[PDB]
Each structure stands twice: as C-alpha cells, then as structure tokens.
Image 1: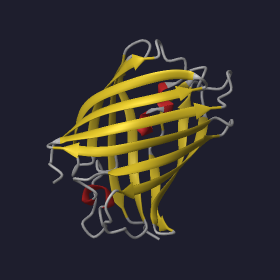
Image 2: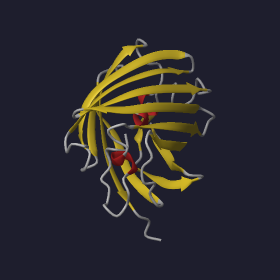
Image 3: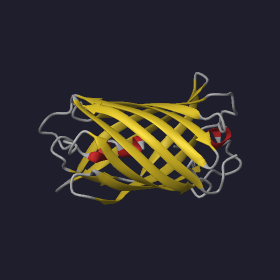
Image 4: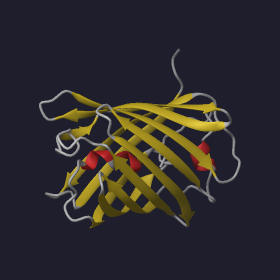
Length: 215
C-alpha cells in the first residue's frame, strides 16, 4: 500500500492571533527512508505577520524510518488513513492546537489541516518573527488509555539568541483498528530549505527515524 516514493498534496486553513490564512502544499517523500520535502504556497493572508516556524510541524508520521520489530501504526493505517490532534503550548503563553485528517489515493497523500493559535504576546519572538529554526527533537510515543500518544519538548532557536520553548502533545487515531505499538521514540529534524521574503513560498524538509530507548 505505502509506495517507496509517495507524493503529498495538502491544504491548511488557519487563524493565529486573529490573522486568518490558507496555505497549500505539494511535495514528495520516501516513507521507508523517513524523508520528505514540501513546496508550500500562501494562498490567503497577505504577508503572514507571525513566524512561519510555528506552522512547520503541522505540515505525517507515515514518513518515518521504522524498525520492523516496532509496529508501524502510521503505515498500517493506510489506505483508509489516520488523523492527529496536537496541542502546542509555548513558554510565554502562546497556545496552538492543530488537527489533520490524512487520506490516500494511488501514490499520493492528502491532508486537510486546521491550525489555530492564540495569546502570542505582540512583543514575543513569534509575532516579532525572531525565530531561526527548530532544534532536532525526540517524540516520546506511547499507549495511554488505549490511544497512541506522542509528547515532544520542542525548542525554537532565537536571533541572538538562546531558546524559546514549546510542549507538543499529540493523539494519533487510525480510522480502522491496527496494532498499537509498545513505547518508542521518533527522532526528527525539520528545516526550511529556502523561502522568499515574506514566506509566501517555502521549501520544507524533514528527516525522521523511529527507535527504542537504550534504558
């Protein structure tokens, strides 16, 4: 079902501190390699007045290099697909919630993403566009009350700079019942490869690999 080379088509509808926006994307990834690249275009919301970095993790855990001995909840979820619900709490009270419904047709993945952010201080590094990139991270994957959950302590590097923290909490729900995996970790690095002046056009990349804890 999951082809070694999978295309990506997405649509994100959002609002951050009241600013409404629509972003559309087209890309390709090698799901077994855990690599993917997206070309993102700002369709609505003129020049985005907030850091584009807060959006990047919202733009698919099917794109992870999974060891065989660890059940792959995300790749088994297809063709029907899966959904995810994420909470993103920033250290200065900025709060984001994003939802994504992921479907599949042929060699292509389709995402309907909803992104909502509020309480970002006007002088904070998000509204001030003072963020550089996300630091490489580790998502702790585990089953709590019969659902697959993912936690990640994220850190945005700043101009100067030091770090600006965010806590992610995600719920992964496959549409049809599949094998829930034992506790594992997913290491990732998300990067903006290129962009134009106002981030109207962005080229995004991600490399992700699953593994067990050496404990």
